[PDB]
Amino acid sequence: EVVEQVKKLFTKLSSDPTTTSQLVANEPASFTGSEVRMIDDDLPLAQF
Amino acid sequence: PVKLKAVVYALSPFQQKIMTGLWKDLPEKIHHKVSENWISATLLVTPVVGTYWYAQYFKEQEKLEHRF
């Protein structure tokens, strides 16, 4: 029943044949050792 | 303890070049050193060199005037 409803209702979607894997391979993510310290002595608690 | 507010961003030592900065901006480094320090340098070199040269001149004149 769900499959019939879906194939009847979802008929206007884009048809672009681009996987997410290609986008990830085209803009890869990498890790950089680094730190950001937001120093505020007025906050009662420290969170890191 | 002083109450401080600041944001500090830092990069890891293993992600940056360690020695090339020695030789970057080298004309600026030389220019700053000369322009900020030439008075101090003069005030240090001038009395010593002047006193030395005057002493040498005094010794040469005294040596000559005792000859025959």
Image (cartoon, grey):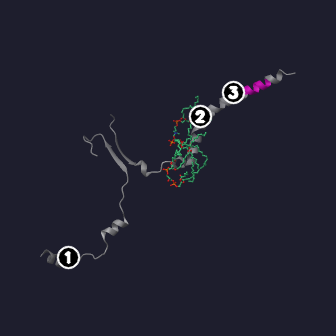
Q: Residue at x 55, y 48 (%)?
A: B23
Quarter of the image that includes the N terminus of chain B? top left
Residue nearest the viewer, comparing A40 with B68: B68
Q: Which residue is mark 2?
A: B40
Q: Is residue B29 above or below residue A11?
A: above
Label ID, residue A10: 1
Q: Is residue A18 left or right of residue B34?
A: left
The stretch drawn in magenta includes residue B58: yes
Instruction: Decide whether the magenta segment is chiefly helix, strand or loop.
Output: helix
Q: What whole-number distance in Å separates the C-alpha atoms at marks 1 and 2?
A: 82 Å
Q: Chain of mark 2?
A: B
Q: Residue at x 42, y 50 (%)?
A: B14
User: Tag 3's secondary structure?
Assistant: helix
Magenta segment boundaries in residue numbering: B54-61
SS for tag 1?
A: loop
The chain to which mark 3 is attached is B
Return the disc, 2 or 3, that comes first in the chain's sequence: 2
Q: Is residue A45 magenta?
A: no
* Amino acid type shown at disc 1: Phe
Amino acid type shown at disc 3:
Thr
Q: With respect to residue B63, does B31 lie above or below?
A: below
Q: Are marks 1 and 2 in contact (CB under 8 Å)?
A: no
Image quadrant containing the C terminus of chain B: top right
